[PDB]
Amino acid sequence: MVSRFATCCRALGLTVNDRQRPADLTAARAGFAGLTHLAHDQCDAWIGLAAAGEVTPAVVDAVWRTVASAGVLQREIGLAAGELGFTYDTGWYLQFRATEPDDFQLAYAARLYEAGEFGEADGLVGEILARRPGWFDARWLQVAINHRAQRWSDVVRLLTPVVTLPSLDDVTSHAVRTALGISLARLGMFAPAMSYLEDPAGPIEVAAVDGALAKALTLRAQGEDDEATEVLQDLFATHPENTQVEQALLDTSFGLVTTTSARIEARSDPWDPETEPSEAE
Image (cartoon, rainbow, N blue to C red; front, side, top):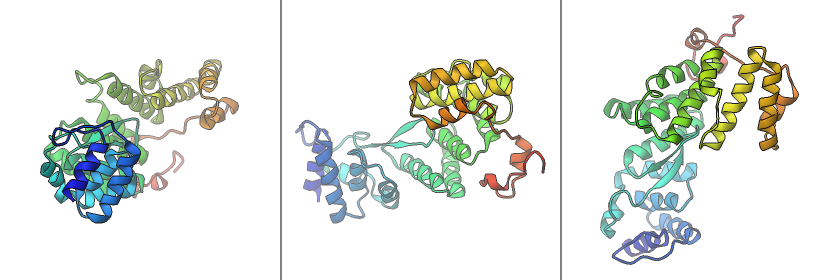
């Protein structure tokens, strides 16, 4: 098992026992996959498979399931901490690197909320934030959970003290400002939204697209129809296969559906937008 693990790690391009080779991620994926049949309960085999690029719900599930043994094989082969890790999607703009149990916990929380298990997700992230309240990754995971549940007021509340933090990098800043802009617009707070969305460009392509779309829909809500159209045309010309952008551009009466904090708070199930009363109700 240990020899196989070392060999699979070397296929990732990691130095092991002072030997290194060029990475072959196709081979690393197949290698670690096979190793999960031998060592089904070894977290490091699953971490390796994810590290090689197979970051599926099944793999994230398995990493979590086997988390007791995180780092056991790593230590057997003498890998320094942080060398073996994988990239996981938060579900909103950002991808994070996972190397430690708490990262695995967040990746699993991401998996859970995407699968509709919002309460379990929120509980796992909250557990972390009780210990690590300043840890950006966990703060963002909470925001992403609330986003998927369409809890716009929570997103704004949570991001209010984040958007002013010093030493946020350009990527993080772009995600935060885009998320806060969108969420404000979803609360009908259009002029506030525009403070963030007026220039939606940034390093995260998907955030630049969402930011521009929300910018257009915000302008439309403010009666700036021709400006909205220009925004949407510029956006559609650069993203001609984007059917969401197409919908908004072709139907000049399509608007952003908005709500309020009070309506959100009145849900009978906090995680289910279907239980949210409409403006009429």
